[PDB]
Image (cartoon, rainbow, N blue to C red; front, side, top):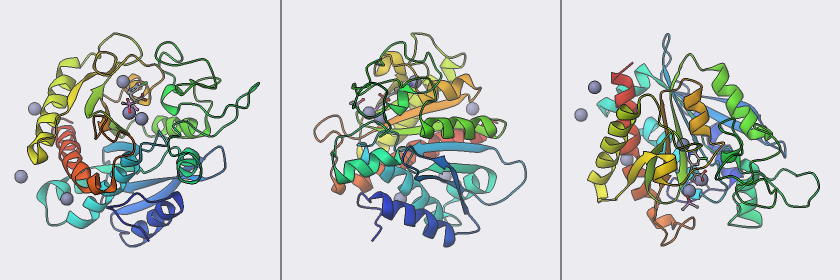
Length: 304
Ligand SMILES: Nc1ncc(C[C@H](C[SeH])C(=O)O)cc1Cl
Ligand SMILES: C[As](C)(=O)[O-]
Ligand SMILES: [Zn+2]
Ligand SMILES: [Zn+2]
Ligand SMILES: [Zn+2]
Ligand SMILES: [Zn+2]
Ligand SMILES: [Zn+2]
Ligand SMILES: [Zn+2]
């Protein structure tokens, strides 16, 4: 049984991607952008009413297997789109004028593993030459100062950068999709947990994006909007100085392709539950996070 207020296993999420598409054909289509190491289809939902030459926002969840609130959020975003389209002026305007690509779970193999074997798994489940240690950090696997800081060369480490940038099937598939849709994708949003932050480039070096001032102000206003609901306190800024320097992240990579609005969201909490955020917090976390995402979306829409 699928529920938006619980964590759902991969079989349930996959079935939900079919059913939500099936039930909302005027707003949702579903493709597979490739397959995982283990051969699972990486589903992608395109959310929006058809129209000509529509710009797009790309959002993924579930890079990191254990960050279950991420996967729940992408699902929540789709829930909102389908529930409030027609009733709420903003979301209606967004879906009429933009398309949202929502990739509910990037690292499916890892996610399955968190359900069957090890709740605290992070990485992919691919093999590494010369060791039995499994997996690559997908957010250290992009071609963005690849493997240079805040990433490990050791395949047994949690931030393992992999054998080469885009060595993972999942990261290759994501990058290929973005590269193939670059002239329409105006913003890239990647959802993680935890520590309550809105981060923007760069993380791979202590350097700042050309539109730093604009990103800073947007991130600040998004954090302010998020707090209006439950008072939840986020920090924000360039990744390297706001969370830690880390190379090979998808947001930095996306920004270096020319996607000017590129953010990583690190959802609740600040460590009390960490990755094991209880189900009772799914609704409040997603709701407040909707406010930030809708704020960013509205900004993007108003500054094309
Ligand atoms: N470019 C980036 N932008 C954000 C992050 C933070 C996440 C939080 Se889980 C991570 O460590 O991958 C990491 C990188 Cl490498
Ligand atoms: C606090 As963390 C390991 O999710 O960046
Ligand atoms: Zn209004
Ligand atoms: Zn993460
Ligand atoms: Zn995190
Ligand atoms: Zn970054
Ligand atoms: Zn709501
Ligand atoms: Zn303005």
